[PDB]
Length: 71
Length: 48
Image 1 (tube, each protein chain N blue to C red):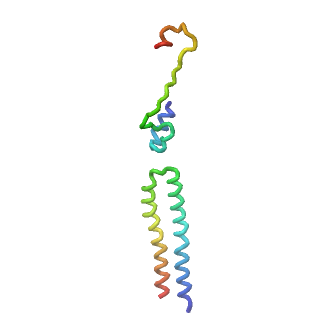
Image 2: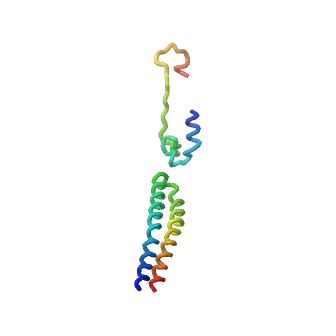
Image 3: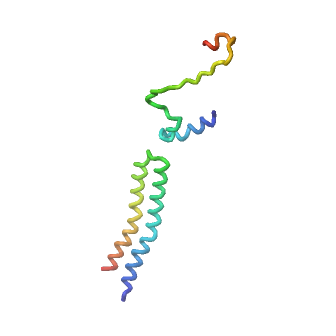
């Protein structure tokens, strides 16, 4: 029936729930840390991104499913 | 003094120590605090 559309919607939404909060936490922490100490900026960002990216992998996984169920 | 010792053992960051703890490289201007007895008869100290 239309259960595949509900599946696609659930995949995208439930994938988006967690990564949004996590990425907010990452960038908030990095901004606060740089504000405290500027000279460490280029290091924390270098870690920031190699953290941040990992999270969206999960989200992207959902998006991948959000198409695999779609077609 | 030991409070200085402990705290300086930490916060070694030059930017963190940019406040007073920093060592000016140019040293273009310097200042001397001289404490001299107020009344004489002190002997050779006032002059020394």
